[PDB]
Amino acid sequence: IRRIGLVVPSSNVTVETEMPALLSRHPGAEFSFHSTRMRMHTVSPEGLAAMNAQRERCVLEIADAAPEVILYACLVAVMVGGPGEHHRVESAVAEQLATGGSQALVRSSAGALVEGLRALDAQRVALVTPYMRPLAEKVVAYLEAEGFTISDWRALEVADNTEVGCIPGEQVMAAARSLDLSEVDALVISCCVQMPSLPLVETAEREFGIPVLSAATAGAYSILRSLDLPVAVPGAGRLLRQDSAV
Amino acid sequence: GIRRIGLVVPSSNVTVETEMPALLSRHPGAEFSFHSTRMRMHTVSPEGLAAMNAQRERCVLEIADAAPEVILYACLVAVMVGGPGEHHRVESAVAEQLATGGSQALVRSSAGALVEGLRALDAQRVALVTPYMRPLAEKVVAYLEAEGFTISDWRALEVADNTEVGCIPGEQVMAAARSLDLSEVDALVISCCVQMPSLPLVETAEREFGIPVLSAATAGAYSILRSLDLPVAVPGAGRLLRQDS
Ligand SMILES: [Ca+2]
Image (cartoon, rainbow over all chains, first blue to last red; front, side, top):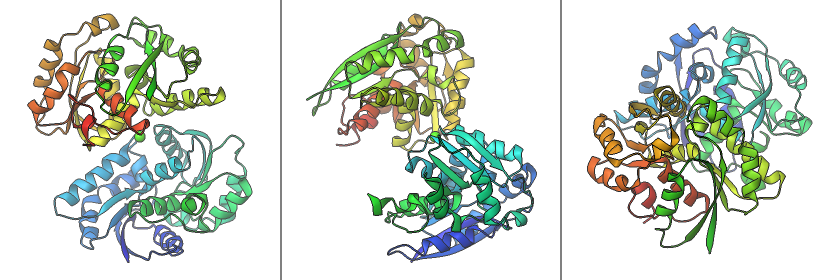
C-alpha cells in the first residue's frame, strides 16, 4: 500500500474522487489517500490568493501522515503565479519538509500536466477549462512558457468551485467538439482539478483520434512515474497505458 | 567512431569553436568533429539579435548537409530574449526543419543545455556572470526564473560588441565571481554567454568556492554527451562534466 498525500482546495471534491478511481485499476499496486484542505470557494485571483497562503499549515498536516508522495492538487492557484511557479511551489514544499525529516516526494497538478504533455511528445495543444476568461488566459500563458502552443481553448466561465464540480460530461464534451483539433497533438479535456472528466477521457480519445488527458490522469501519471510503477492502467487514455504499448 | 557535432553560431562568435572542442577532445572514450554555419550578427542588441535569428532556417539546411549527430543551436542570449520557454520553441522549429528534410540529428540549444545542466546538478539557488547589457542581463535572469531557479545575485559586464566580449580577460570574469555573495548559492554560472571566454577559470572555481561551477559552453558539453549517450567524464571542468566516474 502506497500512501499518497493530497493537498486540495477545501471545496474540491473531484481529485479525492478521480485519483482513487483510476489508480484502483492499476495492475499490481494498491493505494491509499490522505487529504489536507485549504479553504477556497470562488475561483478568483483573490480566492486563489487566500487559499495559497495556507500551504505552510497543510504541508505540516499531511507530512504527519508520512506519505510516499504529496500531490499539491491546487492547479489554478499555481498557474495564476505565472511562468514556472510550480517549480517554486514544489520547491517551497520540499524545503519545508526538509525542515522536519519527511521523506515524501512532491508533485503538483501543474507540474504533472506539463509531464503528461511531454510524455505524449505534445507540442500543439488544445484545452477545455471551466475557468473565467482572465483565468483561462493565465493557464494559457503558463503553458506557452513551458514550450507548448495553445492552438485553441474554451473557458466555460463557471466561477463557483462547487458548481464546477457539477459540470456534466456532455457540457464538457460539447466544448471539446467545438474545438478545431486538426493540427493538435493532445487535448486536455479537463485543465481543472475540480471539473469532472474521467468517464470521458477514454471515449474522447476514441472519437478525436488524438491523445486526451486531464489534470487528474496526468497527476496519476506523475504519481506512478515517481514511485517507479508501470504505467499500465487501462481505460484512462494512452497516457496511462504507455508501458502496455511499449 | 568520430561523432559529428553541428554548430549554428553567430558569425562573430569565436569562443564556442574554441572551448567546445577544447573540453570535448578531453574525453577518453570518444572523439569528436565540429562543423558550423554562421548567422551574421555584430551587435548583441534586440535589433541584431532578431536579424540573426531570422537566418536560422538557411543555417540549418546548410548544416543538415554535413549530417551532424547533434546540432547545437549556440545562442544563449539570442534565445532568452524571446521570452520564457523560447528554447523549446526554437529547438522544436529546428527539429521540424531537419525531419522535413532527412536529417536525424538531435537538437540542443545553449539556453537549453544551461537549464539541463543546472538541473543535473540539483541547483535551485543560482548565481551568474554575464557580459551583457543589463536590460538583456535581466531578461536572462527572468528566463531562468521561469525555469524555476532563484537568481540570488548576478553581475553584468555591459559590453555590447560581440567582438569586445570574446576579447574578455579572465581578470574580469574571475573578479565578478568573487564579487557575488555565494553563501546560499548551489551553483555558479561563471559565464552565461557562449561568446565570453570562461574555461581556464572553471575547474579551479569549484575547488576555490566549494560549489559546482559551470558555463553555457560546459553545460552544452554536458548536454551533448548526454544526447550522444556517452558517459559524462571530461577532465578539468567540474563534477557536472565528470559525474560518471
Ligand atoms: Ca520548463
